[PDB]
Structures are given as structure tokens and as C-alpha cells.
Amino acid sequence: QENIRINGCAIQCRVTTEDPARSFQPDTGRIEVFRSGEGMGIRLDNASAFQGAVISPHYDSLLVKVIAHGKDHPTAATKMSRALAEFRVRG
Amino acid sequence: LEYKPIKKVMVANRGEIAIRVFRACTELGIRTVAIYSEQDTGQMHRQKADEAYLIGRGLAPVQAYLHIPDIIKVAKENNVDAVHPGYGFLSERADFAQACQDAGVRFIGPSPEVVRKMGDKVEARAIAIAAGVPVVPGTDAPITSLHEAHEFSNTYGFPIIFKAAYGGGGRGMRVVHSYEELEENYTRAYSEALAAFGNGALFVEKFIEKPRHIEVQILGDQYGNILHLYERDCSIQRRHQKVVEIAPAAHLDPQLRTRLTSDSVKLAKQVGYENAGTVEFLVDRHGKHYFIEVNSRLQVEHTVTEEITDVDLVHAQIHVAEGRSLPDLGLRQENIRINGCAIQCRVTTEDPARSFQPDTGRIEVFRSGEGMGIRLDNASAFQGAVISPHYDSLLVKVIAHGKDHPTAATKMSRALAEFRVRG
Amino acid sequence: HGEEVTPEDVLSAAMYPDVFAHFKDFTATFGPLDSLNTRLFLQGPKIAEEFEVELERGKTLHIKALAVSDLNRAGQRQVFFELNGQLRSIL
Amino acid sequence: HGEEVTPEDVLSAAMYPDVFAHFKDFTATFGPLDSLNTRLFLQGPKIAEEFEVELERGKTLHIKALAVSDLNRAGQRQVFFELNGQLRSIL
């Protein structure tokens, strides 16, 4: 318990393939354009994402698990706003 | 006290640093401008910023980024408030800096006077002798007679090293142990210096077996306030160049690292530097440090300290370029601390077998292996990527942040295993 | 049809409603036009012909047409394109 | 051309050394044979058709043919293949 010390702040997000308009109803399809975005305080986790991929509805619609570290909460919020801008998932 | 905020910044280079500055600006919400040459329309930087403009229509690609007036006119036309010159291309150019001041466009970096004062080795030697740490010991003046070398071998020590001035070649590197060896080595060194080269400005220095050059990073405001970042180790060298990097100290005496810290702080105060810089020393096995020089632009391994200290350097550069003082940022000694072990590698399309020569061609398959504490910076990596045969051969930079130095070593070894670049 | 209505657009709809509906529908389903060369507008690109499209002030698009697939899924032919830094495929 | 050759292969070299050199060259170049279907080995994959390639007890991969481009400038063709989920262009 005593060696480990709290260090910094971090925020974790999951990117989904739900239609954020109708009912957050998950969408299905095939990827066309995939662009990934990394920074200093950025960290990405790829589930099934690549160029010309196919997702199957038998399993979850989890594509990217992202964690951003910073020296405070607002820094992490802004860092993730920028990171979400950086990706480019088209199709 | 003076607040002159930034509305747009212009990058006058190409590649990974361009992406770095663009992401920093968009994280600060700074309007971004990108510039490309005719050959280099395939990178990601030109389409990653908001705007892309061509330069050097007929000039050579190696000098395509070296044309000041055109990029000056582009900066003016796009209402560029501040420009950052990056590294290697025009940061060493004092003409461009004074021109940047002439156009009124804010400059990201020190004042042109400091850059010009650095100049040749002679200003550095004069300033180091006047006010600074001892420089590598030896002879300030050239040796042109047997008697200077004989007296300096008699006085300091029989084993000495002959080096040749006004030349970067290693052919002027000779070893002296004894009188009979002294005169013969002096004679042959003088012969080679006057034959292969011109002025034989030979210098006598002490016998050095193992150099270990150690780097110090310095930030300051325009208000006379100076913070050293922390130290970095570069014991690894192919022959004279960086291949991998180790920021936390392998074998450093805290007294000696404290001496280096205070010396770098006082010398930054002496120079009166205004932006990002670094002082590199050269230590012996015994425990003596010697100045080598200072880089006035933002070093490549800067971001390595970015993992050491949990502070951004490009943001701090932006903020001092605005006019803020470091205490406004809360940039003081006590909060910045060593946090973790760091190792640095860079991938190049070169074959380490015969002559470390680069390879050119088209990559067939590439995959990513980003780790839990493994940070990746992609220079030019995509499906169907073609590497230019005239520009640099840098593709990916990998950062390993491990709880231990062997921790990062094994993690980044696994990362090397997972990466696949074929063809 | 959304918020993108201006007084001149109102006038254009007022004089000619039906063709305006057709035009807005077509532009929406096909993206911006008039940024094409007339060659591309009527003839379209020829395979192994690279070309350039300008979209905004600094906005350059280098498009090279790689190949055209055949009929696979009840009349779904695939085509292959190369943009600066990426390869795309369209059905 | 021996880097892991076996004494059994030494016997083979004693048998037909010239044909030995030819087979070794061909093997180091195009890789191992005798992992392929007879029809696939002789006439080859079909366009808009996918098959399976076993490598080891577990190394299992799949290949689909997409299309074939035309000779570009000097008798060079671009062929599009789909691996497990990734795409490869082959010259």
C-alpha cells in the first residue's frame, strides 16, 4: 500500500458504433477510412479496427478504448477533445 | 506583464515535428498552416493542418525548404503572426531569424542576437573562458613546432592527443606516449595536416579513453527566469550519431549531477538565453565534466524529458513566445520531478549489415503495436507509403516508459517484435 | 431540408420549386459540385490518370484511379482510389 | 546456398547438384511449396474468390482475390489480395 502513490489524472472513453440520434441504436457496416491519433498524453487500444475491416453484430461494437493522462482533470478533458478530433473514421 | 496573444503559427519544415506543432496548436486552438514541396505531397502533415501551400517550384527538394523569401511571403499573405522554424533546416540560419523579426512576425525561439553570438566555436570558447565551466583541456593556440607539443607533453603529461583544427575529419586524431613517439607522431600529424588539409592548426589535449556526453535542457522566459528541465544520457553512439537514447541517469553521482545542473543554470544566465536550449557536457571515468556546446533549437529527445517531468515543452515554448513568465505557468523547481524510466528508439530504412546505408522502395505491410506505456510518433507510415530518396529516412519514433530501465527495455523489445515492415 | 436556407435560396425555390428540390437532393446525395473539371464532370476520370481537385483556399486533393472491379453482389462493382497517404475503395 | 541444409539434403546434392542449386534458388525465392491445393497450385486462385492456407498446426490464414490492374509502364501489374482482414497490393 505504501510504495504506490497517486500520480496525475486520467480519463477513459469508449468509442461505439451506435446511432447517437435515434435511440443510441448501434449501427452496422464496413469501415472505409481509418485514421488514428496519438499524442503525449494520449493512449489508444485497438479492438478490431483497421483498413477495410468487417465487424460482426454477434459480438460487441467496441472499436477503440482510449485513455488520456494529464496533470489535472481539465487538461485531460481538453486532451481528449483534441484526440477525438484527431481520428478519422469514415463510412 | 506584456500580453500579445498568438492567433496563428506557421511551420516551415516537414514531418513529425510539423505534426507535433500542429497537434499542440490545435490543442491550444491555434490556427494552423502547413507547407510542402513538390515531391513531398504524400506525407500526412500537408493534409493534417488546415491549409497546404507549395514552395520551391523549380528549386532542388533539398533546398526547396531553404528559400527564405517565398516562405516569408507565404507567412505574410496568410497573415502569419508567429512562425516556428523547427530544426535542421533554417533554425541555425541567423539570416532567417533577423528576417522573421524584420517582417514583424513573431519568432518561436531565441532572439537573433543569441543565435548569431553562438556562431563559430570561437565565440563559444571565448565565452566559456570568460564566464562558464572549463572546456575540454588542451591548447587554445595551434601547435606548429615540435617545441610547443614537447613542452606541453613535459608539463601536463607524456600521453597527449593531437587533434586538427579547421576540419571535422577524424584523420587528425593521433596519440602520443613517449618522446621518440612524440616527435614522430608530431611530424607525421603535421605532414598530414599540411598535405591533406591547409592550415595545420594542431591542438594538444589530454588523453581521453571513454567519452560519455550528457545533456541538460533549459527553459526560460523573457523576464530573466531560468529553469533547467533535467538531465539525459546518450552513452549510445553508432559512430558519432544518436541511435537510441536513455534519459534517466545510469551511473551519475548526485554531487556531479548537481554540479552540472547549477553550472548549466548559471551559464544559461550568462548567455541570457530566452527559449528552449540544451547544454551538453563530456564526462570522463574519473569524475570531471567538460563543456562541448549548446543547441539553441528544440532537441529531438526533448519529449523524452516530457515523460520524465510530466510537462509539455512545446506548450511552454508557446507560452514564453506569447510573453508569459514561467511562474505564471507554475514552472518552478519543486513540482517537476523524475517519474519513470525512459528509452528512445528511431526506425530508419537503412540496412545495418554492410554500411548502415538506407534502403529505398515501397512498404508492403505495416502494423501498430502501441503498448500500455509505449508512446508512438509516426513520421511517414501508411499503406502504400513511398519514402523519398532525397529527404530524411525517418518513419517512426518509439518511446518506452517503464517502471524500471529493464522494464522499458523488455517492453520496447516486445514492441520491436510486434512491428512488421516488409519489402 | 435543413437549416441551409438563405433569402436568395428562398427566391430560387419560389420561382422554380421542383428543379430546386431535384438539385438540392442531388447535391446532398453527391456532395459539392462545380469544383470539377468539365472533363471530370461529363467524362469522369480515366484509370491510371492522376488528377487534382481544389476545394478551399489551401485544399489540394491528388486522386489517382487504380482499378475497377467487376460485378459481385447483385450489381455492386467496386473501385479503387489513391489519395495522398491513403488508399480507398468504393462500392 | 546452404543455411539450414541437412545431410539428407547433402545426399540429394550428391544426386543432382545442378538441379539441387535450381531448387534451392526457387525455394528461397518464392518460398515453400507442398502447402497448396492441387488445383490452386496449378491453375491458381479465382477473382472474387477466397480460400484458406494452412501454414502450421495453428498458423491458419485466408486469401481473397479482388481484381488485377493493367500493365503500368514496363510490364508491371498491380494485384489486390485480401488477407485475414488486411489488404495487400502485389506487383
Image: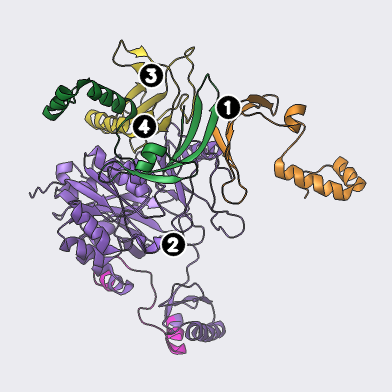
Chain colours: A yellow, B purple, C green, D orange
Q: How many labels were placed on the picture?
A: 4
Q: Which mark is residue B284?
A: 2
User: Over which residues does the magenta segment extend?
Assistant: B126-152
Q: Quarter-wise, where is residue D43 in the image?
A: top right
Give the amino acid type for the residue marked by disc 3 in the picture. Answer: Thr
Residue B55 image position (x, y, % from top left): 32, 57
Q: Give neighbour class at mark 4: few <14, some 14-19, many 20+ (Cα, 10 Å).
A: few
Can residue B68 be spotted in the picture?
yes
Q: Which chain does the residue under circle 4 lie in?
A: A
Could you say whether the residue bearing mark 3 is in a helix, strand or loop? loop
- According to the picture, the residue beneath numbered tag 1 turns out to be D84
User: In the rendered structure, are the residues bearing label 3 and label 4 in contact, judged by CB atoms less than 8 Å apart?
Assistant: no
Asked if residue B325 is among those painted magenta in the image, a careful observer would answer no
Compare residues D52 and B125 and report the one nearer the observer.
D52
Give the amino acid type for the residue marked by disc 2 in the picture. Answer: Asp
D90 up-or-down from B106: above or below: above
**Distance between mark 2 and mark 1 Cα atoms:** 55 Å
